[PDB]
Length: 263
Length: 257
Ligand SMILES: N#CC1(c2cccc(C(=O)Nc3cc(Oc4ccc5nc(NC(=O)C6CC6)sc5n4)ccc3F)c2Cl)CC1
Ligand SMILES: N#CC1(c2cccc(C(=O)Nc3cc(Oc4ccc5nc(NC(=O)C6CC6)sc5n4)ccc3F)c2Cl)CC1
Image (cartoon, rainbow over all chains, first blue to last red; front, side):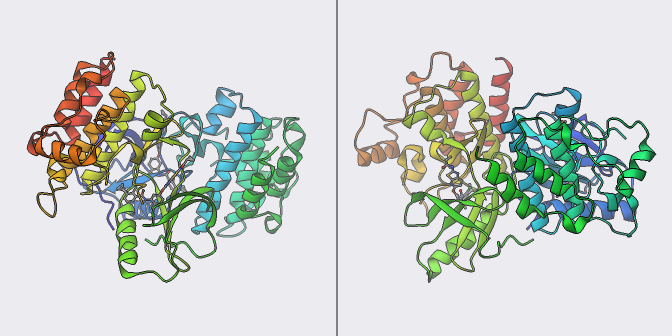
């Protein structure tokens, strides 16, 4: 039941940025692969725990819309090897190059993301940092949900715009939940339908945190493109509800999208 | 690690193929999936063993060019769930609806196919039945190797045809199969199309009197490709290259193009 990659086989190449913990490179191992590795002499016991936790999470997943984990190595460095994604993140498409998707596709990118999040939740995985730059649009047609951090381009302002109000406040030692993820998804939906990030009219970062937490500030739903189906706008609204128990789970969401995915 | 899918989650849909050694439908499980089932409710021992063996092989593979295994189920009927491929198989493209790929694309299809076979061999998996129908050209772009059968002589190497030992399948036997696939890609046809008799083909390939007609390769097929093709089809087993070399060749071929 083994996924260790023996030493000397992975050829580390270009250098892409910085992951959850380490540094991500473009590599070669039975084809193009992505290699996250801790560039250190000796791992700390906590660092080695992170590694174990991440390998433990990725090895539970086998789904077209989740980043394909291929193996790991511990022989010179700690290193996770995943598939290599071609193209760019949703964030880059929507907010950097201003890509011009047709609604039929915007809904598809939504549908696929919904599939992957449904899957993760099925296997008791809470993503905790879902956002558009963690959605790679592979080959320009296939969502691949990852946890890149800085492998792909970074968001405007941790990462504030996708945090549900209860996550922002930080009352509990753990405010994260299937529903915290659903709120995140709700903002991704907002991005897709508006083409924009939320709260464009505020330049102060602390003010956004304060207000979204207090439920004084909410995404401006009037900005959704006029050819966006009322089902999708209504669904967006239900994912963005401020009370978390009032948010739908993904089985429901996936249904709702699959429904409107005719006409 | 546990991949058993709880019961009453897979929604079986349209029927895709029957062969008596299983049935395959299209299904819904966290999006689209392929589901291979066993018809008879109370299964046999030989049936149940093949399931454990197939699931055992599949769960060892995580690579972009191999069909993604997603899970298994037993608690109503035995069933294996993989990803659902959109598009058509290589066989179907070449021989049924006769798609004309440009030469850069054909090379690429071959590159990926070898890329996956490299992966399998690395994990000590001999395919034993590589052929154009077992290559799926997913979304007209990514090659997904699989095994959708439920024999096929045209891809069978001499030493396999002759049933030498109880085991004549080797990495080299797959490399031969790969050669026949390269022939299909470059000629656009199946081999020995001028012969209608299966016994004779078996006898003839077996004895080494017959081998594919490399004169039929597209005019703009590179000299390096025609040569690689010849090497992969060498009647003598030990002369055939392994997939690390083949990739090395294919990749160098694409560079000057
Ligand atoms: N399981 C799981 C999740 C999870 C939890 C924790 C960590 C991860 C994770 O992502 N690990 C990971 C990420 C990695 O980052 C990647 C992966 C592919 C990739 N492709 C790129 N392409 C480009 O930049 C364009 C020029 C062509 S950049 C790039 N970076 C690498 C290794 C990992 F383990 C993931 Cl997926 C919830 C999904
Ligand atoms: N790993 C591995 C290997 C291996 C060994 C044994 C069995 C398998 C295997 O394929 N199992 C398997 C296959 C299956 O057949 C499939 C899978 C996907 C699929 N997509 C289709 N698309 C279409 O027909 C057109 C409308 C677009 S049909 C279809 N059928 C199903 C379940 C399996 F376990 C595989 Cl991949 C050695 C290659």
